[PDB]
Image: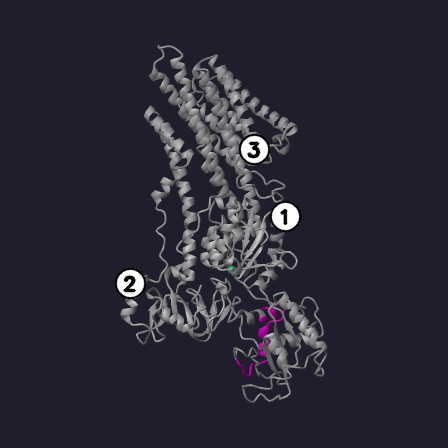
Amino acid sequence: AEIYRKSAAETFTQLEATEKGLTTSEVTKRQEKYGFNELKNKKKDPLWKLFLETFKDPMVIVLVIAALVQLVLGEVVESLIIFLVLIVNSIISVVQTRKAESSLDALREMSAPVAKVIRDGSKQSIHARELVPGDVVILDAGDFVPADGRLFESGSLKIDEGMLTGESEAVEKYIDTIPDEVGLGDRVNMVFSGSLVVYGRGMFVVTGTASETEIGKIAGLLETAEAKQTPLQRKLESFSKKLGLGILALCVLIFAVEAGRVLLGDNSADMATAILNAFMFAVAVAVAAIPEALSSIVTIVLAVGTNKMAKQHAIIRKLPAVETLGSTSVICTDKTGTLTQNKMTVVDYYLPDGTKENFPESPENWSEGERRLIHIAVLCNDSNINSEGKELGDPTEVALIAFSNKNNQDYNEIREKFIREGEIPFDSDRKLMSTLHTFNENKAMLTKGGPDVMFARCSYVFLDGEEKPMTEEILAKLKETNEEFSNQALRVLAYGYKRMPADTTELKLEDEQDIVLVGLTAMIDPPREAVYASIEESKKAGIRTVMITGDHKTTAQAIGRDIGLMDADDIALTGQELDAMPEEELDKKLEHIAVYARVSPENKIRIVKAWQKKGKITAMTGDGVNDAPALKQADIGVAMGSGTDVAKDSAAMILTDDNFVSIVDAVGVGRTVFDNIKKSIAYLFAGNLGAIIAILFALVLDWINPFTALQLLFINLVNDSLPAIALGMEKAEPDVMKRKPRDINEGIFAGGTMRAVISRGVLIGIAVIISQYIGMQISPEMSVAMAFTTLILARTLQTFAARSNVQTAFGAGFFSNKYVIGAVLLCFVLYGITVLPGAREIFSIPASFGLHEWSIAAGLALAAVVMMEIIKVVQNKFFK
Ligand code: BEF
Ligand SMILES: [Mg+2]
């Protein structure tokens, strides 16, 4: 924050080193003191730590207590089933946590393997690991920067600072000390570790190593990035705490009821039998209320959504990440490589003849001026594309010839038509290269460079021909066009041709006057064709989009206004302004600011953290290294296929096809996934509530347990899991994309879903109560069998009613959800397996369970479902 401001001698004196180098004793003492230039990998959570962390869930705690109670009671099989369920849930959660945590290693491969360091007066290829502040490193083209440092001798050095600015653009490096504070991407006189050197030679003095570097700061932010809780995960945690409190209250009520039946009853009833009955009732309540298959069902629905969006070439590493997309309220975005294609292109153009909007794609129909413009654009080129669009040098020349080829006019044919006869490379202050290649029977010299230099050098122009050198009207029009392009943040290069000499004798400075401007071409990183549609859909979906980019203020403003991110002539927030902004000021000015420019990776993490502080599920989407801290910090991080590997790892999603529409598609798929998950959880907990009501009513009447532990485990694991998955297979709501993002504190049972849960559970419990009463009219074992049958069949047929909370199954399509019908049929098969003579004893179903008792129980379950439909109709007609 101060090294770049200080002079080269000042920072040399600060580090106690000279330009010659440092001795071996000094370098080894400085290596032993805060040395070891490398990104220390985080030890990260071991497997056992994650295992014990997964055991802190209230549902897991209640299930563990129930399993221990069953093991003490002698129910070895049911306790082992509960233990296996807990093992499966913990394994699933730990696997998901490991997949999320795979966003590690910080990509230390970005750091250079070697480093040309002059040590003890000798130049050696010392490995970048053994580098210390004070070490003087020589840089050349194609050499990764080993450590952060300040320039003191650099000859036309250019560094691809694509891991802070996020752009593969060769940033020019000058040794002059910066007198004023500049942004992290504008530090001209300071190299940064992990940034490739594109062109030129340089030699700097290291000022930072390991975590003190900017890539070190990025690695530190990645390591300290908060493991965000998924909105489904946080809703389930809150409802799990509530359900654990409710189950503890239910067990307290059970023990109090039994203690009352003993103390207020008679001394004949032994304490041991009553306490044993209380323990069985409490463990049955725990098993029933806790959905043992809930984690598996949620994981399966999330995997279904992940596969659905992987069909669109968007790999979602984290299973809850699709849900996190569904609950997204803010989409933070990078510009270079994420909004734009990270490929410079020519978008606009101008000639004194005029501008025909879009450049014609037919060279046969091309005008003379346009043809000469393209010619003096291609034959003066520096880059090339030969195989699979391989880029030769700077993206500016690549942009020029890509625009030339995009008009169905291959540049290679023109280059072979007009052989190069000498050229001058870039001359720093002289932006004009002015190649002197011989043309077709004209021997005209062609030039290309910056706007201002071209306009100052020449006075002629190509209006219709060799126009007389007047410089008022054409100059005004040219300047107006250039200023308009600059206001559009369009990079401008002006080209011309001179032919007076027609000799081409030497290759040196020539008559830089009278180059006869024929036109100039605009240039910018254009937004992806899918970006505008994605922005329009996100705004229609209530999701605001925020641009966080390393580009200058002008380019970010132009891109935001191009895609409708900002208002008319809005003002973006520079990275410097954000750095000078206290967190309170940023929070006060967060909704109003929609585009951030010239930001550092820590600035991106700061913006994402601030947006998450406002209770909004932030969707940071990026492709560069600078986005990786923000990708990890965001609740959902979205990467691109062409983005860097660290950005792909740090982001939950990876758009392999770089389709920005896939981001809004993921938002919609996640909304549908959360609707289906809420349907499945509502169904599971309505069945659980029915079982709980039946058990409590049996308790208060001194009745036998409606369902044993094995029966409840079977229902919750194989007879509710399949219908819950089927309801997770539900079709998308018609207005799934028009809904505002769901509240982060909405709760799992909200917006009429709690009412449906309560009604369905109450009716299921009432049916099981009536069935148990009818069974007790026969025998307690018959009561258990018929209560279990009624509960299992009511929960099987509850799939139809749980499809929608306002529209009945008869009216939403009874067979529209083929998964629901398949799950209902398979649950019928499973229940028929239960009433098999061999398996009757396992499910406490006596051999006397005749077809009359089955008919009564099945009719009670069907009446429960019919009354559930009737209650749904009464609810959506009367009160909402
Ligand atoms: F590469 Be970006 F636009 F931060
Ligand atoms: Mg980028």
- Residue located beneath label 2 in the image: 32
Q: Which kind of residue does numbered mark 3 sit on?
A: Thr
Labels 1 and 3: the sequence-earlier one: 1
Which sits in the foreground, 678 or 613? 613
Magenta-span inclusion, residue 408:
yes
**From the viewer's perspective, is residue 845 above or below residue 47?**
above
Quarter placement of the N terminus: bottom left
Residue 540's tag is 1
Q: Secondary structure at mark 2?
A: helix
- Residue located beneath label 3 in the image: 753
Q: Is mark 2 within 8 Å of ligand 1?
A: no
Give the Cα distance between marks 2 and 3: 62 Å
Q: Is mark 1 within 8 Å of ligand 1?
A: no
Which sits in the foreground, 327 or 364? 327
Which mark is nearer the camera, 1 or 2? 2
Q: Which kind of residue does numbered mark 1 sit on?
A: Lys
Given contact means CB atoms under 8 Å apart, are the residues at marks 2 and 3 in contact? Answer: no
Residue farthest to the left, as pictured: 25
Give the Cα distance between marks 1 and 2: 58 Å
